[PDB]
Amino acid sequence: MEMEKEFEQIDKSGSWAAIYQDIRHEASDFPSRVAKLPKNKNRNRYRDVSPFDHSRIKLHQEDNDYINASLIKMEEAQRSYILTQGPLPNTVGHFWEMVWEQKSRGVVMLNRVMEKGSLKCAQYWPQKEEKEMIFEDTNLKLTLISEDIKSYYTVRQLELENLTTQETREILHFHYTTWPDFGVPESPASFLNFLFKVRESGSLSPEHGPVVVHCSAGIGRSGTFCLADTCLLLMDKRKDPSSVDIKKVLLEMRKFRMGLIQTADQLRFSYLAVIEGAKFIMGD
């Protein structure tokens, strides 16, 4: 069923809550035993959001290999993403350790450091060229190279140095700054414009490791980003673009991380973004 028609159908009948609850009922449940170990309580921002053991990212240290992050592997679309929580004060060094070990080219950030008067993630990158950051627990140096501030997003060039080997790499930070404190955006135009800028950079391409994407919990805004990307890529690839079923793709992605898409408003917005973004994918 053409999603666009399915869309008007749900909208006229006002069934978005009932659709979303079907998804929550059919979604996978797998064990997350490593996340719940007592030695990791201060590595988890929220008690009810954990990586499954089968898909979690492991740090390459013998000490404690745990970080609240998951590998979403999309086999038909040939895309992979790492979804993670906003870094905590005790995990900023683990975050950049992961970015290095997994060979990512880009980091995607969908939240502000402060929202609704409270801190949603640590200030984990440097704000001035001449004031670099050193993560002594994981032996890494991070320097701001350049900054391009636009109306709806900011792009930053960062240098990450492994102080153990003195290798350096360029990391691109893509920061969407205008998601509202409550609800979802009214039009998906600026979110789609942002997604295409990430694509154009090479950060989503198979010559690099998976992009790292995060919001506060790493499941809501972050889920919207990867669901919309994967769905548009499948409409490109398939003989019949109408065969792309957004609810089935979301359930496949939830085999890899719990809770992706947090509200019925986020579900609706994901439909809207795919429908509108298809009006370039099909040749316009």
Image (tube, rainbow, N blue to C red):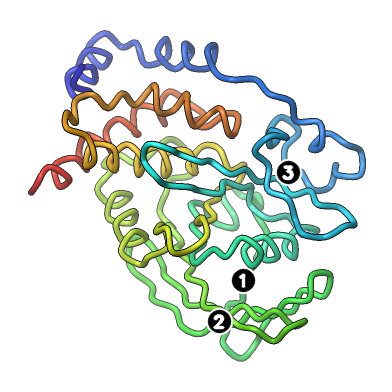
x then y, percent, for residue 92: 72, 62
- Judge whether 79 appears above or below 172 on screen: above
Structural distance between the alpha carbons of marks 3 and 1: 19 Å
Element type at marker 2?
Answer: strand
Residue matched to label 1: 125
Residue matched to label 3: 45
Q: Earlier in the sequence, mark 2 or mark 3?
A: 3
Res 238 quadrant in image: top left
Label 1, residues with CA under 10 Å away: few <14, some 14-19, many ≥20: some
Element type at marker 3?
Answer: loop
Q: Earlier in the sequence, mark 2 or mark 1?
A: 1
Q: Quadrant of the N terminus?
A: top left
Residue matched to label 2: 144
Q: Residue at x 43, y 38 (%)?
A: 75
User: Could you tell me the amino acid type at mark 3?
Assistant: Arg
Structural distance between the alpha carbons of marks 2 and 3: 26 Å
Q: Residue at x 24, y 40 (%)?
A: 237
Residue contact at pointers 2 and 1, CB within 8 angstroms:
yes
